Image (tube, rainbow, N blue to C red; front, side):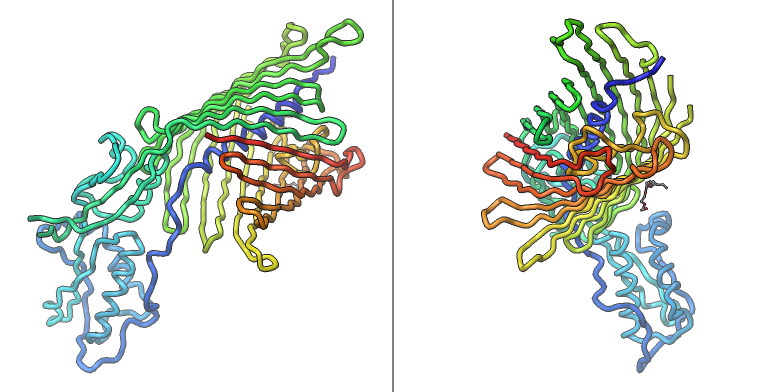
Length: 536
Ligand SMILES: CCCCCCCCOCCOCCOCCOCCO
């Protein structure tokens, strides 16, 4: 007997659409604007200079101020570490007033490097009488979080901000907490000195002005893509609920209906996503329900042959920011997933196509800023069971930058996704190319596939003379290789030209494309696509 999932095309397109949807929801979360706060005024190539009166330093130490425990100072030994590490070998040199000023400025830049923007390196110059350079730290702390405007529960502050009153002010934790609050608020954050009767000297007040974002958001989309003969028609209802349980949380709902004339299929899809932050951590869970019907409902033969089936997927996600700055953000994550799928023929179940799978994902993601350019990507390791240690490597890379093109503002965009499988994969685990999600300019009725694969999408958009409009041209490329692939059919090259416009909560995206290079079994026909969305 010949085993066959006649629905494999519709399920591949659903997975690609699911991945695109999850990326768009993650991209909706506002990040902190990039900056370069640790800006060296003077480069510190040479701190020691030849000076009129100087003292020979024989010890560089960090010395507690009044009321400072040495556990408080243990966190700041990197300041003295950096001093002693400097290739000018400060220890044993003759230090006058100008070099001492430079050594202090260097240790303060190092303080700002690690994010302590309200702390200050001071010198206790009395012990220089004995050749001892003794540094001290004015530890700047947080006195009060002040909500000048907007409502926020005490629990929201505790879970969204990884810091509390009385902690040491660090810009990495301020930015993290600010990003968590910007999921549900428009946020204004200011640092001011704390006042006592008329100041608290070592303390700061965090002034927050909050304005809640629209609680309920709707997105209705219709898409009509295909070739000049056949096409697919999609309808999407997206609902975004903002801060429903007052936990800086976001709940997303999506219902999709599709009519694919390429595979004479009808598809419905339900998707729910919940996400809440806990300081540097992030918790998420999602669920997808997918159903299809395939065949001719009223055939000429009088023998109706309908293939239909359902598929469910549940996911639990946990990620933690491990490193961040004004120009980068890095996090590690772990996923737990369970999948279940069954197929039918005229309401009779095909037993050998009943599939339950489960497994876990481990990965790391990074985002990097330089100027107005954004670079972000991830690498993922997956392992899943069946009914057997099937390892899958996944990777992602995206790059965006503005640039001038014939003296008009423009944007360049590159999307790259790659998959490497050491072992044989089942059909659904393969990497597919050709269609709106993998290589544009192809209709997707026939896709190339391999156990290993990668595509790179490239696109340039320029502003139209009309406001809130832009033209774009795109060139995409796909590659498949490894098992489940046959040579000579391993490459796709498509091109797309189109336009996009936004008219007062109405978004249009239309493109016409064609396949440039393809194996003989691929049509290289002309394709069109029209997308309309309404948010309110
Ligand atoms: C440590 C592994 C991280 C994940 C890497 C997966 C991306 C590797 O994809 C390889 C698939 O290549 C298919 C054919 O490639 C031909 C073109 O190659 C030129 C660019 O490498």
